[PDB]
Every structure is written in C-alpha cells, then in structure tokens.
Length: 103
Length: 464
Ligand code: HEM
Ligand SMILES: Nc1cc(Cc2cnn(Cc3cccc(Oc4ccccc4)c3)c2)c2nn[nH]c2n1
Ligand SMILES: *[C@@H]1O[C@H](CO)[C@@H](O[C@@H]2O[C@H](CO)[C@@H](O)[C@H](O)[C@H]2NC(C)=O)[C@H](O)[C@H]1NC(C)=O
Ligand SMILES: *[C@@H]1O[C@H](CO)[C@@H](O)[C@H](O)[C@H]1NC(C)=O
Ligand SMILES: [Ca+2]
Ligand SMILES: [Cl-]
Ligand SMILES: [Cl-]
Image 1 (cartoon, chains in turn purple, red):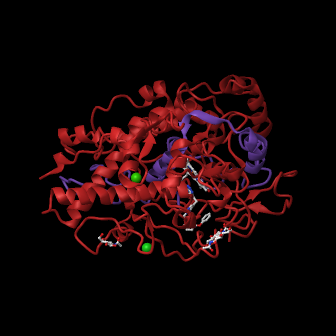
Image 2 (cartoon, protein in one colour):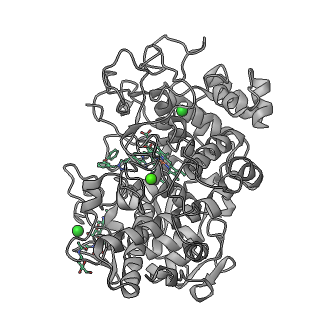
Image 3 (cartoon, protein in one colour):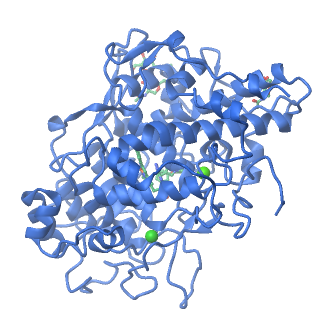
C-alpha cells in the first residue's frame, strides 16, 4: 500500500489506506441492516412451502408483479421533465457501482 | 441447471407461477433464477452475503474494468499513445466502435442468425444488454481516446502509461461531475439533495465507501423509467424510418443494430429527444421488461420487477418497514397507515392483499410505490438509501475530483466546465444537442442548442 500515489488502482484496492479493500472489487457488500433469511443464515423467504415471514404467507414475486406492477402499455404517461438520457445514465452509473455475480 | 429446470435445488431459486397468470398458463413451468454467489460458500456459521465484482467508486470502471487482466485487454498495446482498443472489423461513419468479446455462449448472436454480430467488450460485462447502453459505453471509449490524443499533442514526451492514466483520471472526474451536479439532484429533488448530499468539505478516511446490499436493489427504481421502445432519430430529429420505434423485447443483446442499423448517433438522439417513462402508482413498469425481458435469448421471457423481488429475498434484505425505520421514517403497521404513507389507498389495499403486512413488502416494491418527492423521481425511502449511498461514495473516495492533491485549482476550474451534451458533440456527428440539464431537456427543438454554444474542456492546465 503506497504512502503517496497519483492514480487509482484498477481494482480499487489502496483507495482507503487504513482498510485497503474498502470499495475494491470482488468483495462482499456491506450490510446496513442484518440479513433476514427463512433459516436465519442462508435460505431465502419463500424457499420452503408453508413457512411464513413475520406470521404471514410469502407472496409469489410473479403474483405481486401481476397484481401490482402490470398495466396497459397504451396508458403510459411520458415524463414532461425527464429525457430517456436520465434513464440511460442511471443504468450506466449503476454499472460503475455494482455487479452481483451468479454461478 | 437453472436455465431449464424448475426444481428448487441450490443454486436454483425458480420463480413459481401463480394460478390465472396472464402469460404463463403452465403452472408446472417457472421463471429461471440463479441465487447470487455467496461470499462464503457452504458455511453454517456466517450469515449469507453477496459479492460486488466491481469497484464501488464512481471511477468509470464500466469503461476501464475492475480487474487488471481485463483492464489490460481493453487497452491498445500496439503503441505508446495511451488509447483504449477499438473494433477492428467495424466503424460508425469512421468513428470507433467497442471491440467484440470472445464468449463461450454469446447471446448477441441469438438476436439475429444472419447478421452474426457478437457482444461488445467493455469495462463492465453488461455493455451489450441494450443498444442505448452500448451507445453510452461507445461514447466514453471515444472520449478517452480523444483526451489521450489531445494530451499527446500537449505533452509529446509523455508515454502510453502516462497518457492512459491522465485521460482515465479526467474520464472518471467527468462521470463524478455529471452524476453529482446534474443526475442526483434530479433523482432526489432539492430537499433530499441538501439532506443527503450537503456541500463537499473534504475526503474522510472514516467513511466506508462500499456499496450496501440494499443499494443493489433500491437503485433498480430506474426500471420504472424504462420506455417500451428503443427510439431512433435522424439528423433533423425526426423518426428514423423504417423501424423508428423498435420494441425493447427485440433490442436486448442486439449488438447487430449498432453495427448494421446506423451506429450510435440515432440511438443518442432518441435518448435526448424522447421523454422518459413517468413512474405513476398505477403505471409502475412496462410489459416489455415485465413479460418479454430477454424473450429472444431464453426459453421463456423473464419478469424484471419479479426478478428484483426474488433478488431481494435471495439477498436476505429486510422488508419495507425495517428500511423506513433505518431511514428514520414513520413505519406503517396496517393498510390505513400505508395508505397515508403512499398518499393512495387503492395501492395500499393492493399491496396488503399480497403481503399481509407492510413489514413483508419487498424493498423495490415498497420503494417504487411511494409518492415521488417534489422535483425528484423517488420517494422518501429510496431518496434516503440512494442519498446515503452516494454521500459515502463521494466523502469516502480519496480520488474524488474535488479532493486536495487529485487535481490543481486550474484543472478543477477547467473540469467544472464539462457536460454530457459536450461529450456527445466531441465524439459523434451530432451537431444539435440537449440544453443543460440534459436529463431534464427532452423536447426538440425547444430544449435543444448548437454545439458551438457549449464550452469545450480546456486542457491547457495539463501541459507539463
Ligand atoms: C434499461 C434497461 C435495463 C435492463 C434491461 C435492466 C436489466 C436488469 C437485469 C436483468 C438485472 C438483473 C436482475 C436479477 O436477476 O435480479 C438488473 C439489475 C440491476 N439493474 Fe436494471 N436494467 C435496466 C435499467 C436499469 C436502470 C435504468 C437502473 C438504474 C437507474 C438499473 C439498475 C439495476 C441494478 C442496480 C441492478 C442490480 C445490479 C447488480 O448488482 O448486479 N437498471 N437490471
Ligand atoms: N446483474 C445484472 C445482470 C444483467 C443481465 C445481464 C446482461 N448482460 N450480462 C452479461 C452476460 C455475459 C455473458 C452471457 C450473458 O447471457 C445472459 C443472457 C440473459 C440473461 C443472463 C445472461 C450475459 C448479464 C443486467 N442487465 N442490466 N443490468 C444487469 N445487472
Ligand atoms: C437481421 O439482420 C439482417 C441483416 O443481416 C436484416 O436483413 C435485412 O432484411 C431486409 C428485409 O427485412 C432486407 O431488405 C435486407 O436486404 C436485409 N439485409 C441483408 C444484408 O440481408 C434482417 O432484417 C434482420 N433480421 C430481423 C429478423 O430483423
Ligand atoms: C491501436 O492504435 C492504433 C492507432 O490508432 C490503431 O491504428 C489500432 O487499430 C489500435 N488497435 C486497437 C486494438 O485499437
Ligand atoms: Ca466503480
Ligand atoms: Cl444492506
Ligand atoms: Cl474487435
């Protein structure tokens, strides 16, 4: 970890000098709240049929999407004060911050 | 085997199909889902956490990469000019395109058999996801090479490494400037902007710069801004016929459209001169992502909103009320309370029928359900999560553009003059662009200006 530097490393390593992995790539996310899993440590809520979350049956993501998210395309309201550029920068920005790998 | 099996065996967490589904009539079928890689595989001790494969810093890593071998490949090692590699087979009116990638299973090749156009290669692996994103990546690649070229004529004694590094430093700064000065004030609105992003003082080594697990899900609010078409406009900002409105379910991974259907200029004009979708409580997200997401590259069309909800569960994220409490916001306990929070009873009723308690509402669902803040595009809860994350990314970054020692007073004074419409001018054939703010300006010709009017970045303060 160098005592003086002009440029960023590619991996983000050495940005914070005290904890040099902070903000660096291929590292676990920080948690702002403790995780909530069906078994306490790994199984997701909805994994086991019949197992309730906070005394309530777990709703199917597709059922929530069908009942709440779904709407007729023809009804779409364009934003009078936002461009698609606002959407596209958001996703481009997202891709500078986080990517969660899968198997 | 998550791609084709419906069995719930690790790492598969398939999305079960409800009865009377509008699209999937086979209840034995499912929506494919792979659980995010655990930080600690197979452990019975640790509480499962996920991995961030990227640098949390607003450092333009979607351009340069977050890993040194990739970072090296993306570079032009044929000379000492500090450039990023370009497509060796194609150009966009003599202008550079991203190099292609050499993938085992390439999805872009599936979007069009005859065209045989593979995925593009960038700092981030999702560059070919949609041509609009590819266009933004292609724009930044061009901007690096443009900077590396100008700096070479300014400092001929500088080597490839010096040139690469200096341009990269500028590009990273430009992303930080556009994001904090123009983008976030329009996401959060002014009061959340003052609350979560007060005037920058200086770098602080006690501010954790890491991206929080919740942030990976809360920042998906952008899915509510997505339009059901990719819009392509000509020189005169008129619908580029034929196919000026291509359904999004026909553009995912369609890198051939960039190469063979006009380059990035019509895509960028479409982004600038078309309004974003407005998030309304009865119009949350379009069916192009809700029913037909990746339809031409998968066995079945995915549901992006449902995937976000399954993801928060995979990630073990607490529900809506736990995040409201974290934010120091009132926690609704019943439908009547939630109605007050959302300032909408129909949506609270709708939500309660599904979840039974506001404690169980999935963070993306709850977040996008809230009424938008004045002059912002998120509610209090997403403004808190987003605002909190970006303050940490700014105050906890030692290479933040405003930090002492990163740039000189003159270089900072010069950088303050940059803007996204100017970047477009310098790296495309587009001569008429959005008036600042680019993210607000959406109507041609009303919100449009000529390139000449926009101030260029003066690199004089960079001469050694
Ligand atoms: C415009 C087209 C877009 C498409 C097709 C798209 C697609 C996706 C998909 C498929 C995922 C992974 C879903 C999963 O399995 O959980 C995803 C994740 C994500 N998206 Fe979107 N998205 C788009 C736009 C946006 C926008 C505009 C934003 C923000 C403004 C955004 C932010 C995110 C984030 C933060 C994630 C999680 C990233 C990670 O850590 O891996 N997306 N999106
Ligand atoms: N974490 C995420 C994930 C995606 C999906 C995606 C897009 N490109 N890649 C990389 C890539 C590389 C190689 C094969 C590949 O095939 C597919 C195609 C369809 C689905 C999955 C894989 C895709 C994954 C996002 N899209 N936007 N934001 C996103 N955030
Ligand atoms: C796939 O891209 C091909 C180009 O390879 C497109 O082919 C064009 O099709 C139109 C008629 O639709 C013809 O007039 C052109 O001559 C074709 N181009 C070439 C070079 O053959 C085709 O449209 C794309 N496929 C789809 C289904 O959109
Ligand atoms: C490397 O740079 C030279 C100079 O422009 C260029 O001619 C060559 O195509 C570049 N190679 C790549 C891979 O971009
Ligand atoms: Ca980054
Ligand atoms: Cl978290
Ligand atoms: Cl190539």
